[PDB]
Image (cartoon, grey):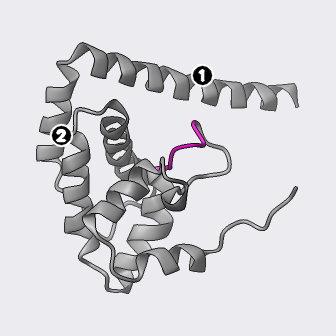
Amino acid sequence: MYKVPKGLEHYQKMFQKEVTVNDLKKYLIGSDKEYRITRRDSYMGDISDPEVILEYGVYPAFIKGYTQLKANIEEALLEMSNSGQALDIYQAVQTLNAENMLLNYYESLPFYLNRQSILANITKALKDAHIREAMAHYKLGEFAHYQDTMLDMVER
């Protein structure tokens, strides 16, 4: 069934109010359906897409004046990246990747994440076999999923 997609105002209601570190963790992972933000076409629909969170949620809210989001999302990423949990580390990497790709398109952003500690935590996690293997597998999955989308367009 066609459903009307979520409006800009839909995200505004979630992000122009008190938002805690813990809320931000739950949004960025999005395993809990109540905090799950995704694009229509996206690898692993049971998990959220940080790029949609940044582009349509956090950055508009920050510009409006909710500028505590910067330090709080930093703390959120700090805790996710030092958690020893593969999926939490993956969404932290995916959030860093999203900033980069958005920076490259827009040529500026309303704020820049302090990424050194987070990056340091990710490298520590990469030393662990299970973590880096789980992350390789997610990464390879995302490639396969994108390639399957290119196939359909070839068919048409």
User: For the stretch drawn in magenta, what is the main secondary structure?
Assistant: loop
Asked if disc 1 and disc 2 are in contact, CB closer than 8 Å, the reply is: no
**Residue drawn at (42%, 61%) of the image:** 54
Q: Position of residue 27 (x, y in %)?
A: 42, 58
Give the residue at mark 1: 144
Q: Is residue 6 magenta?
A: no
Please provide the residue range marked out in magenta: 44-49
* Mark 1 to mark 2 CA distance (whole Å): 28 Å
Residue 104 in view, yes or no = no
59, above or below 116, in the image? below
Q: Residues within 10 Å of mark 2 (few under 14, many from 20)?
A: some
**Residue drawn at (57%, 37%) of the image:** 44
- Residue at disc 1, secondary structure: helix
Residue 57 left/right relative to 97: right
Q: Quadrant of residue 10?
A: bottom right
Q: For this rendering, which residue is in front, 60 or 82?
A: 82
Q: For this rendering, which residue is in front, 94 or 112?
A: 94
- Placement of the N terminus among the 4 image quadrants: bottom right
| Foreground tag (1 vs 2) | 2
- Placement of the C terminus among the 4 image quadrants: top right
Q: Kindly identify which numbered label has been placed on residue 82.
A: 2
Q: Position of residue 47 (x, y in %)?
A: 51, 44
Residue 81 in view, yes or no = yes
**Residue drawn at (22%, 39%) of the image:** 83
141, above or below 78, in the image? above
- Residue at disc 2, secondary structure: loop
**Residue drawn at (29%, 22%) of the image:** 131
Q: Position of residue 13 (x, y in %)?
A: 51, 80
Residue kind at label 2, given as amino acid type:
Asn
Q: Is residue 48 magenta?
A: yes
Q: Position of residue 122 (x, y in %)?
A: 20, 34
